[PDB]
Image 1 (cartoon, one colour):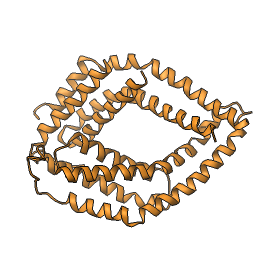
Image 2 (cartoon, helix red, strand yellow):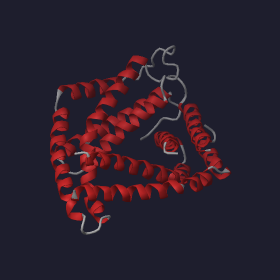
Image 3 (cartoon, helix red, strand yellow):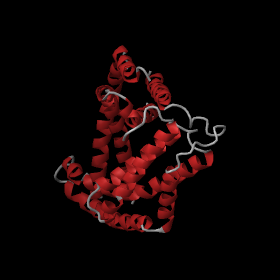
Image 4 (tube, one colour):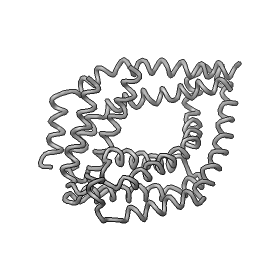
Length: 296
């Protein structure tokens, strides 16, 4: 993504949406033809990033347009959830049967055949949504709206006319601050993980304003904090799923198996958090951001 450093933040956020919506549209065929699971993944990342930035930078667009985009994107994202789960868990097939004693492994067959049936249903549901008018009406209106370069009423869109550099340095700095304030359980790790996502999204949005070498230095600096939190949440999610699948004797032993194995690992991940954040919460970190943001 290529930003104009002296353009208003309204201009640069529009450029972001142009970019992310073009990703959504580019990935529709691969999803519909079921080429592989990466297409839906990239489609979801584009939505998540759009929603995140539009919310972090509230006041860049007219308030009615902002709520309309956010509500539309939220519902679009929601539409992708069931199909994404289906792809995701089927992809864990080799891995899941590898955690189990060879005696519990065959009891996972009905579980994966259920997943394949779910995949078929969700694929059809989502494709029917992608080829309908509600989706295409939304996307057409969205593209049309993001083509509008004219600045909105600054009374109710007070951020729109501000210079990007200013906004970039202020928002990143505040996002880093939130991470540290908050880092200094379960609920603490879930929240902190979102703090880091929000920081990462801003970095990736604003990257073309920086020298390449300091964006990477900063993202490498965050990487183990983000790996910790991301794995901890993903395992929680997996456990929540496997939990639910139980309510619906061999198969039960197998899932109790996976559940137990993932709970174990999640506690180890947990235990290693404090070390990692304490290493991130350093004077060096705060300098690396100084170097990134200097002169903005």
